[PDB]
Every structure is written in structure tokens, then in C-alpha cells.
């Protein structure tokens, strides 16, 4: 059950942009989107892959808890917030790729593939380097498939411990106030065309949950704030947030 | 309190500017250092009122009275003054709207013996639950000070309480109050009205990237028109110490 609400295209038009927003009303089990075809087009997950990567790392004990310190590897990189020690909370918040590349090496090719199949995550293909396949390898996932994966995480239904799922959902916390809670992860995929930006997660209300997954063309980094802004425009229009 | 508490008396200016009287207690986790405007009141024990929802939720989860934070507790049909209470709730919304009737049923199901044993295990306040099993934190014998709230919250933060790690994680999720790009606040307000002196509480912590600041405040609350000062005075103090922008 998926309704094409093409009136949302205006929110992309207004901003000089092309993309898709997908919403899922958990209570009514109804889905909405501006573009059914792009909603099912698969892209590299890029930094949104930190969600399954964190889950696998916790379930295998590569990460013991959300306070364990991961030492900076001593390589100065362009994003300054990466050149410091991190735990799981701050590595997610600052999208610290080197920490997650190390997770993937310690998970290893065999267990990564097995768990992604267990997760039904995208096309379950990890072809490429073990520490970069979600950046420039074979894995692809659509907006609707992100939703399906996130729904399982929300319900503690993934095939990892309940504890690992609770810790990752804590690490995904982005915004909270008296009206809603957002747990989400951004992404920006540049190594292979098309360059796109991601925002995936959900909005917790008192009596319902709205899952969302959006991607949009992102020729330059100047447009990155449109990921959250366009999603919220749709969320507001649909009365989900004030 | 291994390190001696530090008294910052300039914080009283934030009480007197509102013609109010109270205490703010802060604990810098990295430095293991406590601060307060009034050491005597910091150690004065009061009824916890709604802040007791934190230990109550922990015990109910550990004993299986609450299966998880999605289990629905049906409205019992009685219409009460606070409109948000007249509806079904789960643990998240019962904490958010401080739905007393839900927590009175938690306490009844826990029962006197297990409730006493658990609060002695937590070393919660004066550990005294004399009174009605479903009202002793409103009008019975239990008392806790602001510094004792800090000690209890610090154990909860570190998962050191004598309940399952899972119960502690769930309650910390339910305490979520505020989150933005700078900080996260997990906290619980309280308003004690059945027994004098009427007082307001705000207890919790601020999570930063690299540190956690625990806080506990209470203040005299002769009328409900001062209730916003629980959060506002605490945030003034947090800002003066450059903890939040
Ligand atoms: C993840 O796709 C990439 C990583 N994450 C990311 C983003 O999701 O936008 C960036 S942008 C950079 C500027 N602020 C930081 C951030 O976490 N946000 C914008 C939310 C990081 C960066 C390219 C990774 C594959 O490089
Ligand atoms: C718990 O102390 C009482 C409950 N909690 C509470 C409060 O701490 O504020 C109130 S005040 C009432 C008006 N606004 C709502 C609120 O909870 N907040 C502003 C946070 C509810 C209420 C008296 C319980 C013992 O009655
Ligand atoms: Ca599959
Ligand atoms: Ca003030
Ligand atoms: Ca003094
Ligand atoms: Cl990544
Ligand atoms: Cl399912
Ligand atoms: Cl568990
Ligand atoms: Cl949380
Ligand atoms: Cl209560």
C-alpha cells in the first residue's frame, strides 16, 4: 500500500532540486511518496551504512558498549572532528568514517555478508573492499528498503541482540522536544555517480511512529542542509510535526 | 562525595531575582567534583513526588510489571484534572506526562516487600516507605535530598543499580527530555503538594560530547505559577558555567 503524493514534488522544485521522500505511517501501515520509481531506485548507502555496521559491531563484541573509546589512528584527515578519540555516540554524531572502517575490518568479509543477508539489507552485496564497499562497492539500497530495515530496528526484530538494537537507537538520537523525537542518520555519497544525499530514520510521536527515508541529487556540498529541510517541509505539510 | 563540595554562592542571584528560594546541585563527572549554591539545603531531604517515577519504573521493569516501553496501560475510565492522564499510555508517555495513576498501579503490583527491598538495594534516600504502598512518595515517609538524587542518578547513568542493564537502558530512554546538536538532557520534574513545604524538583543530567553534568534542584513552590523556574533556574546556572550555550 503506497500512495504517490506528487504534490510534494513542489518542495523539491522550490529548492532547485530532484529527489524522493518516502514516509511510512506505522499505525495505519500506509506508505506515501512523491515518486514511486525513485523510491525504489537503489543507491550506495554511504554513511547511512553506519546503522547496520554499528549493530553488527555491537552484536559481535567488536564494540563493547557506547562508552568504549576508539583511539584516533593518528592520520590527520580533512574533517577536523575526525582527528580525535571517539566513542559510538560521537562517532555516529560526527559520521567518523575511519572508526567504522576499522569496525568492518574486525567484522570481516564472511560475517558482514552473513549479517547483511540476515538483515535483508538492500541487495545484500558487499562486493569490493571490506572497509569501503558501502562507499564505492556493490551494496545498494532504496529508500523503501531503508524504511523496511529501520522498521525492524524500531521493533527490535533484527537478528542481533535486543541490547545492540537499543544501543544503536540511542546513538541515532538527533533531536528531541516536547512534540517529537527524531532518530536518524545522514548520508552523502560522492565516490560514484550519481552524487546524492541521504536522510533516513523515524519520528516518534505520542501515539504513532513515522518512518522516513529521503535521497536527493547533491551535485555540490552546498545543498546538504536540504536533506533535513525538505524532509521537514513534508513532515510539516502532513501535520506530523508542528 | 570524595572531593569536598564547592559552594558557589553567586548562584543565589538566580533565585533572588525570581523572589524564590532553593538549591541547585551540579556534578561534573569527568572531574568528580560537586557544586551547589547552598550546602545545607543540598543535603535536606524532601518527598520525591514525581521524581520517584525513575526508581518506580526501574523496579517495575526489572520485576516484569512492565514488559517493555510499548506495553499499553489502559485508562481506568476516571476523569481526572490533568487531561493528558485520561487516555491510554505506555512507559514513554506515562513518564512524559507524569501520569500518577499508571505509576500507582505499578507500585501496587510491585508491593510493599519488593519495593522496600529494591529501595534499600538502591540506597534511595532514607529508604523508608511507610504509608500507603501506592502513595508513600507523595504523602508517606520517603525522603531524598538533592545530593542523594545525584548519587542515585550517577549509578543509573553507569548501569550500576541492582537491576538488569536492560531496565536501566529503558528508563534512561524514557527520561529523554531534550536533544539538539549541542547536548542531550535526560531528566524528571516533580511537584510535591500533599505535604508542606510544597516544593518543585528537576533532576537529571546533561550529556555533552566529552562529559556528563548531573544536576538536582529543588525550590519552594508556594503556587503553581513558579513551576517554570525549575527548568529555567537550572538552565541559567548551566549557562553561567558554560555547560550549555
Ligand atoms: C557519510 O555519507 C559521509 C560523511 N557523512 C556526511 C553526511 O552524512 O552528510 C558527511 S558531511 C560532513 C559535514 N558534517 C558532518 C555530518 O555528520 N553531517 C553533515 C551530518 C560530516 C560526510 C561526507 C562519509 C561517506 O564521508
Ligand atoms: C509529580 O511531582 C506530580 C506531577 N508532576 C508534575 C511536574 O513535575 O511538573 C506536575 S505539574 C502538572 C502541570 N504541568 C505538568 C507537568 O508535569 N510538568 C510541567 C512537567 C503536570 C504534576 C503535579 C504528581 C505527584 O501530581
Ligand atoms: Ca533477503
Ligand atoms: Ca532567572
Ligand atoms: Ca553555606
Ligand atoms: Cl561510514
Ligand atoms: Cl517484520
Ligand atoms: Cl538485553
Ligand atoms: Cl535515547
Ligand atoms: Cl508519581
Image (spheres, coloured by chain):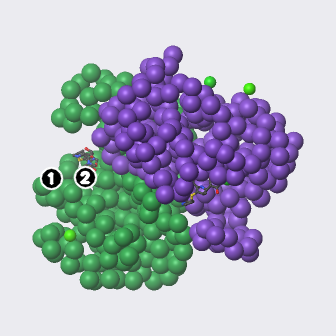
Chain colours: A purple, B green
Residue at 81% of width from left, 38% of height from top? A113
Relative placement, left or right, of A113 versus A231 is right
**Alpha carbon distance from label 2 to label 1:** 9 Å
Residue, disc 1: B224
Say which quarter of the image contains residue A115: top right
Q: Which residue is mark 2?
A: B191
Tag 2 and tag 1, C-beta contact below 8 Å: yes
Say what secondary structure mark 2 lies in. strand
Same subunit, labels 2 and 1: the answer reads yes
SS class of the residue under badge 1?
helix
Residue drawn 21% across the image and 57% down it: B228
Q: Nearer the viewer, residue A55 or B148?
A: A55
The residue carrying mark 2 has its beta carbon less than 8 Å from ligand 2? yes
How crowded pointer 2 is (Cα within 10 Å; few <14, some 14-19, many 20+) is rated as many
Q: Which picture quadrant has residue B85?
A: top left
Residue in front for this viewpoint, B46 or A2: A2
Residue B20 x %, y %: 16, 69
Residue at point 33%, 38% (across, down): A236
Residue B207: assigned label:
none
Q: List x then y, in percent, for residue A79.
A: 61, 68
Residue at horizontal 40 percent and vertical 39 percent from the top: A13
- Of residues A10 and B86, which is closer to you in this image? A10
Q: Chain of mark 2?
A: B
Q: Which circle's residue, 2 or 1, is located before the other in the chain?
A: 2
Q: Give how far across and how far down residue A195 sits, in percent.
A: 61, 47
Mark 1 C-beta closer than 8 Å to ligand 2: yes
Amino acid at each position: 500500500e503506497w500512495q504517490e503524493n506528487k504534490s510534494w514534488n513542489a518542495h523539491f522544485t522550490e529548492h532547485k532540486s530532484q529527489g524522493v521522500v518516502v514516509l511510512w505511517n506505522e499505525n495505519k501501515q500506509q506508505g506515501f511518496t512523491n515518486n514511486l520509481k525513485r523510491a525504489n531506485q537503489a543507491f550506495l548507502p554511504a554513511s547511512t551504512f553506519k546503522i547496520p555496521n554499528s549493530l553488527i559491531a555491537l552484536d559481535l563484541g567488536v564494540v563493547k558498549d557506547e562508552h568504549q573509546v576508539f583511539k584516533w589512528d593518528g592520520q590527520t584527515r580533512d574533517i577536523a572532528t575526525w582527528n580525535r578519540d571517539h566513542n559510538l555516540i560521537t562517532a555516529m554524531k560526527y559520521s567518523v568514517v575511519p572508526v567504522y572502517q576499522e569496525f568492518a575490518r574486525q567484522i570481516g568479509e564472511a560475517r558482514m555478508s552473513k549479517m547483511l543477508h540476515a538483515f535483508d539489507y538492500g541487495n545484500e552485496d558487499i562486493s569490493g573492499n571490506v572497509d569501503s564497499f558501502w562507499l564505492d562497492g556493490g551494496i545498494r539500497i532504496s529508500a523503501t528498503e531503508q524504511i523496511s530495515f529501520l522498521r525492524k530496528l524500531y521493533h527490535n526484530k533484527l537478528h542481533v541482540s535486543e541490547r545492540s538494537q537499543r544501543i544503536v537507537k540511542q546513538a541515532m538520537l538527533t533531536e528531541a522536544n516536547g512534540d517529537y523525537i527524531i532518530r536518524a542518520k545522514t548520508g552523502y555519497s560522492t565516490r560514484i555517480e550519481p552524487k546524492i544525499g541521504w536522510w533516513v530514520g523515524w519520528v516518534e510521536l505520542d501515539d504513532n511512529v513515522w518512518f522516513f527515508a529521503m535521497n536527493m541529487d547533491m551535485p555540490t556540498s552546498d545543498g546538504l542542509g536540504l536533506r533535513q529541510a525538505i524532509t521537514k517541509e513534508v513532515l510539516k505539510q502532513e501535520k506530523i510535526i508542528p
